[PDB]
């Protein structure tokens, strides 16, 4: 997994912004490292558009998982995650319909009343980012390991 530097690896926002600019690509996962307007720190976003304006302009449009929608940020607002490897985590947003992957025989936090046929709406991410809380028709407030969860087609 190609690891990227964070703001703490540079002397100045300008430095770090240049690094992000040099490395960020549409499709990349990024983490918000400096809260900005609708994007809280720690929100994770898929870059959906890059504008190439001034170094500190609102050049990074992501689809933010916790915000649940798109928001433009500056380079210094994000730290690059990159292209997570196959399935290791998917781009799932609050508000998305998810289901337990068929590849999961038993979810980390048990099935409860959820089946593979259950379709739930993501309502929150755990503080560690590894878990989502999902409201299924059969069971609200169901916690799943995000890695065992997938968007419903």
Image (cartoon, rainbow, N blue to C red):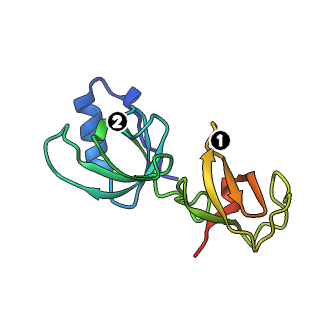
120 or 108: which is nearer to us? 120
**Label 2 crowding class (10 Å Cα cut-off): few <14, some 14-19, many 20+?**
few
Q: How many marks are shown on the rendered structure?
A: 2
Q: Position of residue 105 (x, y in %)?
A: 84, 67
According to the picture, the residue beneath numbered tag 2 turns out to be 37
In this view, the residue farthest toward the left is 54
103 or 72: which is nearer to us? 72
Which picture quadrant has residue 114?
bottom right
Vertically, is 67 above or below 102?
above
Vertically, is 12 above or below 37?
above
Mark 2 falls on what kind of element?
A: loop
- The residue at 33%/28% (across/down) is 10
Q: Position of residue 1 (x, y in %)?
A: 53, 53
Which picture quadrant has residue 7?
top left
Circles 2 and 1 in contact, beta carbons < 8 Å:
no
Q: Going by the image, does 25 lie left or right of 33?
A: left
Which of pointers 2 and 1 lies earlier in the amino acid sequence? Answer: 2
Q: Position of residue 69 (x, y in %)?
A: 41, 54
Which mark is drawn over residue 126?
Answer: 1
- The residue at 69%/56% (across/down) is 135
* Disc 2 to disc 1, C-alpha distance: 21 Å
């Amino acid at each position: 997994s190609q690891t990227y530097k964070k703001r703490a690896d540079f002397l100045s926002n300008d430095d770090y912004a240049v690094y992000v600019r040099e490395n960020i690509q549409v499709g990349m996962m990024v983490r918000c490292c400096r809260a900005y307007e609708e994007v809280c720190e720690g929100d994770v976003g898929k870059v959906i558009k890059l504008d190439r304006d001034g170094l500190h302009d609102l050049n990074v449009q992501c689809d933010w998982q916790q915000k649940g929608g798109t928001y433009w940020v500056r380079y210094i607002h994000v730290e690059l995650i990159g292209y997570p490897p196959p399935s290791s985590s998917s781009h799932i947003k609050i508000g998305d319909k998810v289901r337990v992957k068929a590849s999961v025989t038993t979810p980390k936090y048990k099935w409860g009343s959820v089946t593979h046929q259950s379709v739930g709406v993501v309502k929150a991410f755990s503080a560690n980012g590894k878990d989502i809380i999902v409201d299924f028709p059969q069971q609200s407030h169901w916690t799943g390991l995000l890695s065992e969860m997938e968007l419903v087609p």
